Image (cartoon, rainbow over all chains, first blue to last red; front, side, top):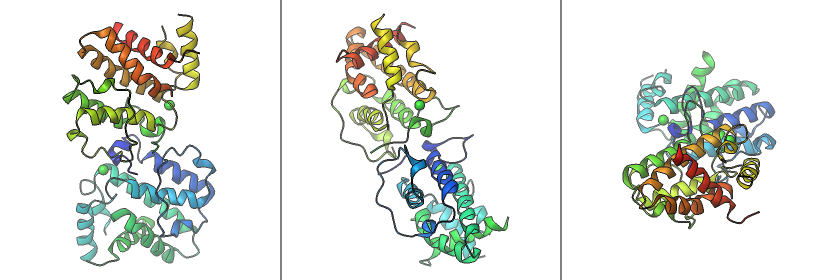
Amino acid sequence: LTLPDLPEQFSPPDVAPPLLVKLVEAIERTGLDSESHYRPELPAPRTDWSLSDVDQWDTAALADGIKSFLLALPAPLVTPEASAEARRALREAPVGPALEPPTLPLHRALTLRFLLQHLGRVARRAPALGPAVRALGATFGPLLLRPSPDFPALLVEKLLQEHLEE
Amino acid sequence: LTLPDLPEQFSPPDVAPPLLVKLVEAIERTGLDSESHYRPELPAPRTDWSLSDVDQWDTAALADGIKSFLLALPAPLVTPEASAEARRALREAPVGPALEPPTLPLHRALTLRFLLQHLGRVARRAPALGPAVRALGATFGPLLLRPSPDFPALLVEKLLQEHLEE
Ligand SMILES: [Cl-]
Ligand SMILES: [Cl-]
């Protein structure tokens, strides 16, 4: 159930994929105070990407939608090249630059930025920022990357931490 | 196996959906002299819309891709409102204006124009223009619209005829 690659989903002056934008805007009107964002379970495979009734969806459906979007891309959001460059920076410890162009291509970088902005807003609603950032890393790491076995989680955790600093 | 609606697939300054653009450009480099465009049989349902290897596809696969694109939209390319306004013009006989904004929304009109341009190029490769235009109407009519039972075919036939005049 594979979506087009990110360059085929949007172009500047748009700064994020419309499907992701629709899910994020929906979920942020209704359910930023939800635990659903933090759930690492994979949703049932999505075949209907119309989002025809997305504004009537419950927070769980929307959170699942965001996860399904990431899993539906033909290749992971964070590329192997970008992963390896983050890994080298993260090991030799700011990972942020590693996940920007040219290292991470424009569409992917924009998409990652849009997602991190959303995940920051979720984190800030939580009772404790640090634990939230950690839980969100554990959930979204594997979705974005698809050697330490927690590297994906640690990378997203650090990227979110850096976003929140700024 | 439903794609996003056309407004979620592209925005100006793009003038057509990238997936359709990729299939059309592919098919027009390789196989404008093919009978495959004229085949009314429905393709197997497509679930992979990555087009990751689209430039290695045979003409039959590409022609099927274009048909699958039209069938994968959440609602027909030509709206019921636009269909009824074309039907009234076509009955009282130029249908063209009826399938332009506001009657047919911007994204759909742009997409229809891009497709008709492609179908015109196919028609002009054929041994006889009139018969080709008729065969293409019969094939694409039902895909675009989803009372005369040949109305969809007649509408596309006339729209293509009008395009070729200009
Ligand atoms: Cl990209
Ligand atoms: Cl539209």
